[PDB]
Image (cartoon, rainbow over all chains, first blue to last red; front, top):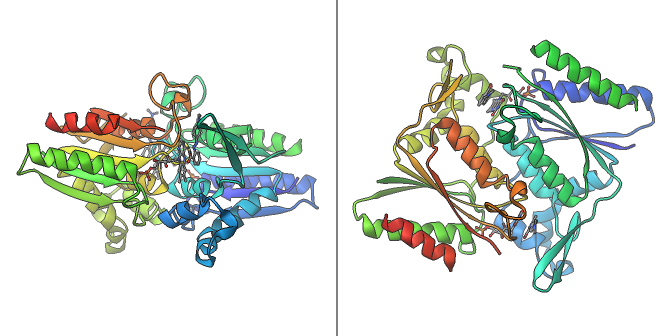
Length: 206
Length: 192
Ligand SMILES: Cc1cc2nc3c(=O)[nH]c(=O)nc-3n(C[C@H](O)[C@H](O)[C@H](O)COP(=O)(O)O)c2cc1C
Ligand SMILES: Cc1cc2nc3c(=O)[nH]c(=O)nc-3n(C[C@H](O)[C@H](O)[C@H](O)COP(=O)(O)O)c2cc1C
Ligand SMILES: CN(C)c1ccc(/N=N/c2ccccc2C(=O)O)cc1
Ligand SMILES: CN(C)c1ccc(/N=N/c2ccccc2C(=O)O)cc1
């Protein structure tokens, strides 16, 4: 299984979501030395937001008629989508920032949801029926939160617009086998982190 | 009232959410001739994402000791927060991008939720009071609103409610254009 690891925390050595994901990646590497791991940084590195030029190009009615300028507008996106297509397992590490994800990860999503590439649609009696184009891929979301109760059955579950939103977006392009490993209370914390780590080691084994 | 208008669409003239929000602002200006409007562009212009440097400064345990470099990391944030403090009514226009908001608006939120400034902790508590918000959003599809078929997929304006609520803005109205009803709804709102 070829892996694409997308890291979304701006923090490096101190990122818990990054560290936990790397725990999973190393463990996996251990069991599968031939396996390819690609890393895509969207936290410590800026990722362009969708511009009007991007929209005009990505939804151009006749795509092969895009100008060289237009293609250039889509070049990063093409690269980012290519990484996804080349992967069987997508691993996203992300903090919860203000009840969602860091803006860099939102930008990454916005680049890789592409008409005619990762999703499609068809016009049925006026309204669009959409169709995902990604097949045979899985996703693991490793997330870290400062507070508690954002998981299932949690007191604050309805406030969680981070990993549940990621599920929705990923599912839209065809990735609906998604596992979320969460550590809470990074400010019981060493416990939550230790549990996430054991969970990730088990997931890596299999 | 003093109004802060935050525009999140990357599109200019073609932006339906921008257009609708400006219909409201012009109408509101007519019912209140000495109103002041401040516009903050977060769609057509890049907003820096939160960096590790931002985190270290913003959550500094002794903020009065911040170095000049740290204050520089928070300079834009202070400006954005100031615009919010100086406003009575916040108007946010935004598209739904992949079941959330454009990344620029996420970045705006990440700049203006600030420890000791728009929220504090002892239990977190909001520090913004006396403000209202109007969210003008447009979507390509249908059924993302209340009682809607796809309401559970909507992490755009419902998420905005959560984040705004955290800092104290809990009087929020959403006007959505899916698929001239929105326009008329907004004209009526501007009259009150
Ligand atoms: C800008 C910012 C926003 C945050 N928002 C939340 C939040 O909404 N809910 C929460 O539980 N923790 C929040 N936190 C705390 C982080 O979720 C927590 O520190 C997390 O572990 C950061 O991920 P990282 O360790 O990979 O950098 C926030 C932290 C920052 C810097
Ligand atoms: C990158 C991108 C993502 C979009 N995602 C969604 C979506 O998830 N759901 C939806 O109903 N429409 C979606 N749309 C359609 C837009 O929501 C629609 O065109 C909207 O009116 C854009 O706002 P604006 O006119 O102010 O630019 C998307 C459009 C773009 C360009
Ligand atoms: C358990 N409840 C109700 C919570 C707990 C934590 C929370 N946000 N945390 C944060 C929010 C913004 C910035 C930094 C943090 C941070 O470092 O924690 C929101 C709601
Ligand atoms: C009927 N349901 C649930 C829907 C309707 C529309 C929809 N996404 N639209 C989009 C999604 C991503 C990118 C661009 C569009 C766009 O231009 O519309 C998703 C789900």
